[PDB]
Image (tube, rainbow, N blue to C red; front, side, top):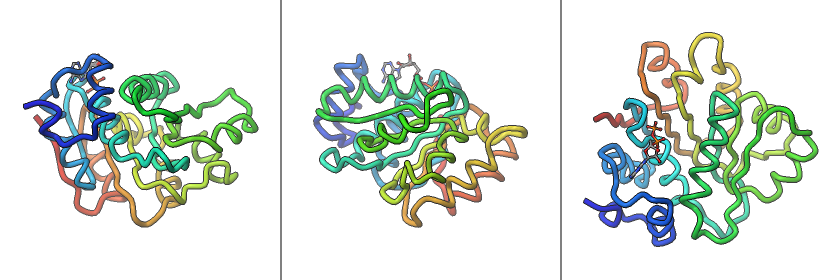
Length: 205
Ligand SMILES: Nc1ncnc2c1ncn2[C@@H]1O[C@H](COP(=O)(O)OP(=O)(O)O)[C@@H](O)[C@H]1O
């Protein structure tokens, strides 16, 4: 089956092909329609199966491009992974004129993040910086409808970002979709995600 059978919009289809993604991987076949349906997803599959591309594709297909507002928030456990996500979104979104996707990490002045957030469809960042930006109302979360956790195991493990993610989650609108993707699903992650997803759909190979 091809990407067309997944009912993606033409700009996303064209972007996928331009970015070198000719046919969906098994996890993409399963997860993309469920993502388009608006369901909360837990996608658990090993590294390299295509999970980053899954959520990036669901995200881009969901965007109202003509509304220059932050509709999608994506968290990553490291600065490098935040940038990797940005690279994937920018590649697949290459046919979407005026797409604004930006990375929010430590080391840039907050005043510059403030300016960048005035033109930002998709915010990608680390939990600490994103929390700070929401607290300052530099990122007003009122237009966010899709909240994505990449490497959710690493995000929510002991000594990581559960407190900040709980806080961010609570700041978001009541009505929203969440996606969590992870290589593993240990008890701590199963338990943590009950805070955010009432009755998630699981996607596994
Ligand atoms: N449909 C596809 N066709 C070809 N290559 C793909 C496809 N989806 C992902 N890839 C590539 O496979 C690798 C792993 O994808 P990624 O989305 O990073 O997986 P994960 O997040 O599960 O580790 C990357 O190099 C990515 O560019």
